[PDB]
Amino acid sequence: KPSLPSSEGGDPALAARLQPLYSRFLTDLDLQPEYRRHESEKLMEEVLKFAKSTGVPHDLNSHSYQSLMVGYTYADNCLPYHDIEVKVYVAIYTWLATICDDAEALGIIDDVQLFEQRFILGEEQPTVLLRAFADQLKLTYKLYHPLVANLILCSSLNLLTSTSLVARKGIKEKGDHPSKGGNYFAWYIRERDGVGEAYSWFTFPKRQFPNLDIPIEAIEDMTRFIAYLNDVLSFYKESLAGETHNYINHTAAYEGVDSDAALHKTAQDTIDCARRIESVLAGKGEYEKAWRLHASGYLQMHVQRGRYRLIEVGVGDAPDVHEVIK
Amino acid sequence: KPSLPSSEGGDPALAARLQPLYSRFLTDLDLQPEYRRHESEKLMEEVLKFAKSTGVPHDLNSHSYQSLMVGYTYADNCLPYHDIEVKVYVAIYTWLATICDDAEALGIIDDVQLFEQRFILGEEQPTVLLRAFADQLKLTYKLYHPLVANLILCSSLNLLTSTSLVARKGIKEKGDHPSKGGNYFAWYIRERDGVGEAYSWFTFPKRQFPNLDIPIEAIEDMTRFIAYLNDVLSFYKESLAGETHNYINHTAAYEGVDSDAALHKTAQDTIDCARRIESVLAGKGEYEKAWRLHASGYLQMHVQRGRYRLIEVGVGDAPDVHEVIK
Ligand SMILES: CC[N+](CC)(CC)Cc1ccccc1
Ligand SMILES: CC[N+](CC)(CC)Cc1ccccc1
Ligand SMILES: [Mg+2]
Ligand SMILES: [Mg+2]
Ligand SMILES: [Mg+2]
Ligand SMILES: [Mg+2]
Ligand SMILES: [Mg+2]
Ligand SMILES: [Mg+2]
């Protein structure tokens, strides 16, 4: 199982190997315009109030608070001009979902695996975390068109399932012993664990973005952009924690190349997705502009937040005093 | 909207265009071994008993009974040596899901669009069809490992959502006016409407196939195999009904080629998927043999069933007296 999150130590040799790729990737993504923030202090007030309402602990310097700061920053950087109820919704979703994402390290896979059957039977979840996530999934329907909320929910449920699959020894065995012809397995797991489809659709809540038809052709590329950008830049922190049965390493295994080759390919794949999204969204009004600010903000979130430890690689920013893991 | 299903007339020019492609495809698929059936009369007794219990009408010579015969034959041909409770489960799921698949022609999009939020809130569904589908989705957990059942459910929910999306004018508009860089949209819709992931996993119920790790690398190729084989061989019946905003025509639109080019490519994509699955499953015991019988049976289901009208193209079998639409 992976180690728990930490702010201590690191891997200087891996950081030296990754810094050149990471610095070139940040430039070559060429995400414009510059990221924006809006009503940042009002957002923090409203996020902390909602967080209190869930009952889920988020003490300063905890893993939970680290994840709350990821969710705050996701909304602040990626959805700056969105309705504040939507920004809080995404911040809180991202807090809870990133804790679930760490379920193997936290020892909560058993209840994560049982979440979906309890959810569709109306059985209350066993923990404060999972009751808050279930309530957050139901809240999606207040803010997103029902078809879009439907897709957000199936993507969110697939997170829990794929996180549980990678916790299985027989699934970790695939990376060590890849089957000939099995190359699609890397994206099979990554499409489901990465929640790229949910995060793509979060850009387009129904009141401000009432026409789901306008950006839909781009969703797949937005999903892959989101998943692949994180696969490149979270490789460092995943290596530190031993959570290395990931898309990069699975890709390297099926393609018979090393992690560095899969990182370079995945970096180029991210750029190719970003350029296709900008072609599809050319002349699509507020949809085009909202996506552009989401992509630019999403790169900066990784630069900024302690979850990704990028200050250690020389491309990120030092953590805030309360976000450092104690 | 598409016309209702019929057994009358056809399109002799389209049939003459497709027959050579279809006869070559049936050979080139080279699906071995020969398809098998087992306890066919006992399965029909059990399927009709369960169908009665749902309350969903299935009168002889109705669209519903045509779909019940697809579900029967799906189980009979593709899961011959599976537990009869699993064969009945798949037949009844297929009956109800293929009626849902026709929701636009039937005028029930409003109900299918609202199914998932009702389902996750524990609200009753508004029609006997959808109450039976909701009950069938919950039954999945008695027969499949919870992670596998989880994936079947998300794939099932995505069917309803993607069927609803294609009913929208702004989604039909994409095929007429494809956006540059939008090529992934064809598979975005087809991954979600095709239920290929559910039908892949139906092969591996938990009592007979207790290790989900064994075939998992193949699921994506089994998903595409299922979707693409149908996209080729159902193009005739979809053309007759005017349900032509499909994977073949979306692919032709984004690639800038005609339907015949997209059909030829999709046929080769099917064969490529079938070969990769047989590589990944080489030496995987009862998993490998169960998949082989499912693929061979799945081609024969399209040959035999009135839903696909392939007797009109010269590659299918004449319908049974009770399955002809009146
Ligand atoms: C690729 C996933 N993500 C969000 C888009 C990267 C920042 C983190 C995340 C993982 C799992 C659950 C929720 C968020
Ligand atoms: C490709 C979809 N399918 C299932 C394998 C092919 C025969 C029919 C189907 C469509 C929609 C719902 C249920 C079944
Ligand atoms: Mg993670
Ligand atoms: Mg994860
Ligand atoms: Mg990551
Ligand atoms: Mg159909
Ligand atoms: Mg369909
Ligand atoms: Mg079809």
Image: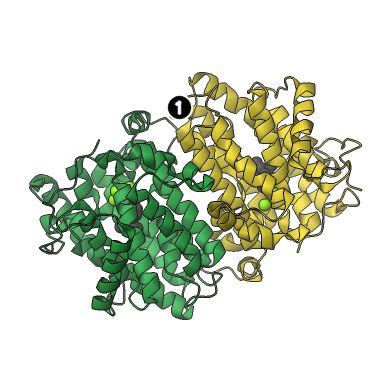
Chain colours: A green, B yellow
Q: Residue at x 38, y 42 (%)?
A: A112
**Mark 1 lies on residue:** B214
A278 vs B105, left or right, is left
Q: Quadrant of residue B103?
A: bottom right
In percent of width and height, residue A293 lies at: 34, 74
Q: Nearer the viewer, residue B232 or B104?
A: B104
In percent of width and height, residue B86 lies at: 63, 29
Relative to A152, say whether B131 is above or below.
above
In percent of width and height, residue B222 lies at: 55, 37
Whether residue B194 can be seen here? yes
Q: Quadrant of residue A253?
A: top left
Whether residue A186 can be seen here? no
Q: Quadrant of residue A94?
A: bottom left
In percent of width and height, residue B216 lies at: 46, 33
A258 vs B113, left or right, is left
> Hey, what amino acid is under mark 1?
Ile
Q: Residue at x 13, y 64 (%)?
A: A320
